[PDB]
Amino acid sequence: QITTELPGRTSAYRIAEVRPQVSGIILKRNFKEGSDIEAGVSLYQIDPATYQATYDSAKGDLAKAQAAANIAQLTVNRYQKLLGTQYISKQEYDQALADAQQANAAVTAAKAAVETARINLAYTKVTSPISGRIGKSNVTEGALVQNGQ
Amino acid sequence: QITTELPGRTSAYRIAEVRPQVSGIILKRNFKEGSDIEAGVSLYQIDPATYQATYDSAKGDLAKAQAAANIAQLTVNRYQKLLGTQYISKQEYDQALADAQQANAAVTAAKAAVETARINLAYTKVTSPISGRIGKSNVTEGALVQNGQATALATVQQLDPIYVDVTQSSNDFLRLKQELANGTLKQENGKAKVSLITSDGIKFPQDGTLEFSDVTVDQTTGSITLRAIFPNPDHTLLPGMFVRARLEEGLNPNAILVPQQGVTRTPRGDATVLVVGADDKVETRPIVASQAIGDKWLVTEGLKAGDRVVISGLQKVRPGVQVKAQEVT
Amino acid sequence: DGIKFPQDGTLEFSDVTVDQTTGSITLRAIFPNPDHTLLPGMFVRARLE
Amino acid sequence: LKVNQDGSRVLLRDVAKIELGGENYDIIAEFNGQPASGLGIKLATGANAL
């Protein structure tokens, strides 16, 4: 038999370096070092103030769009009820239907914006992307972190 | 008990480097150096001019939105009062209600913007993230700062308790783990106790505990790190100093200790002992006393329990000579 | 320490380029580690058949 | 041999085996099958041999 003895270095199957996706100040540390952890648990807690304000603004815009869509839908329903007996021209009904469709599209856009805001808010709760053994924390409570540092 | 001496360095329990979240010229320093700092106490004061202007703009926008909401609400109330006896069509009432809801949503958005502006304005009054002892001021009044700058302004650290990062060779760690897994070494309760030795050699009156033995291996040296926690009430320990740590890694039950006066060593290093058999004669047996504890030697091989070994009067005895045995404590 | 690791591994090639300042090729192997008896970053002598 | 600032160190015993041997392992002397050494005594000038 022919064999070859060689030097080599070991490496982890999956190693993740936890880096923040938002900028702020760490207020808490929700884990203990040297312990196996599960995926999805929260490790740190960055200050959510500004992101909370952005989320509130997005929710307000969504509510405004929802109110506009609701009133447009009410008008469309009334015109559709009246159209049966040929008492309103088809032009008015088509205009109302177009307005309702535009309002629904605006509501969809507001929903997308609030989804983005919610994702940004959830980023502040740093979550371990994988499961495994975690060592020491290179930063303690009170340290300032930057986006993608 | 088995003990190991390792080198390490101390570190603060909680250390924060104060950094600015805004940019501007420092106007005043609100803290005296070397004094304990309560959490949330303002330290510096950066120029609030532009942030004040932003706050005023946000307040004006909020006032505009509030006025619009107020007029919409008044119109809604009047139309609701009129609607009681069908004096106005339902469509106008629904339109007014929709207008009021939209105005209230705009008010909410303006309030959120005002909150963001207020947070930014409050960021200028630099507040200490945590309590503890503050050091010197790396910058003075009149020194420009930028948001998220690398150069920290000051440092606030807690000196009680204290951490000790201690270096352990990877081979020793693996050998100790293998010995523990095979039952050759015991383990009691939880975290292993750790003692400390300072530069002068004074034993630490308090005792810390080891926690969180790391798993990563240093490439350059080939060793892992361990963390120990030590209470520091009298501030006899400071961060960053060099210390020695004594670690107990179990309790060997089958330990054999031999007095150093009864074992001889050849110049090369091999060790032999003078044993006495049942026949009241003296023989020479080779032993392996690699480690010395206190004044005695720990023998790992070549001896068994019940062996009768001489410690005194080796000069007067030659191997192969009948000798009577007397026991001395 | 010269102790043979009880479990065997497998070889999966993962790098064919030759390093500039070493003149060497990096082979890759997978080893099951159920007892956490080998930490990442350590030094091991791999024997290939 | 190599010490970093955080206390990690490399010792000579960790990389090599230290023992006490001879200067050169080139000549092996055996007297009747047993390892042995020797001395050579030369008579000084103007001295009695016996």
Image (tube, grey):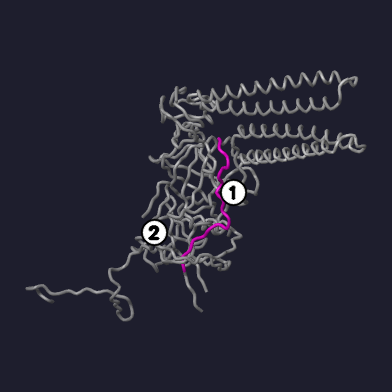
Depth check: B29 or B177 in front? B29
Specify the principal SS of the magenta part.
loop
Mark 1: few, some, or many residues within 10 Å (few <14, many ≥20)? few
**Magenta stretch, residue numbers:** A6-24
Q: Which residue lies furthest to the right in this view?
A: A85
For label 2, the residue is D13
Give percent across and percent down for residue A87. 90, 34
Mark number, residue B188? 1
Q: Is residue B1 visible?
A: yes
Mark in front: 1 vs 2: 2
- The subunit carrying tag 1 is B
- Is residue B183 something that shows in the picture? no
Residue B322: % across, % down:
41, 66
Name the image quarter holding residue B181.
bottom right
Q: Is residue B12 highlighted in magenta?
A: no
Label 2 CA crowd tier, 10 Å (few <14, some 14–19, many 20+):
few
